[PDB]
Length: 119
Image (cartoon, rainbow, N blue to C red; front, side, top):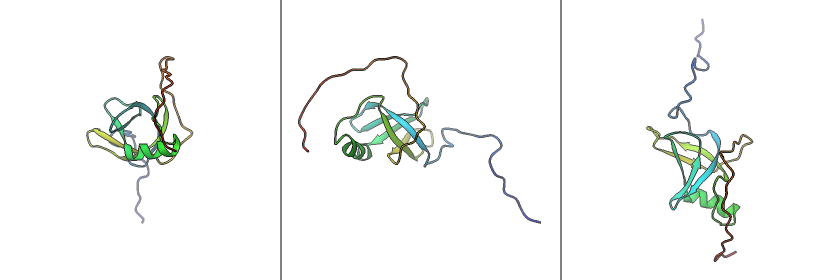
């Protein structure tokens, strides 16, 4: 009588390649780069980089324009996915309750450094 469309898939793929642009995931800054900022996602092989245009925009509006820190929580959303998991495109869209910390031990470097800045 009437056709039928299969709902969900039998066996989930959840593959680094199966990923789709639009998923909200909370990432943490691993290190500060000259071209952008590295975001921790917890994956082997997959690298996530953030553009200075988006990163600087969030920092300027957040840290009134001030360098970020390590292991710091930063909002990021998948905008594009690479074929061979080469480079991932992240962008600031919104935060989410879901958040996990990535630390094996307690250690931090606190240095009271100052410099030029305009308000």
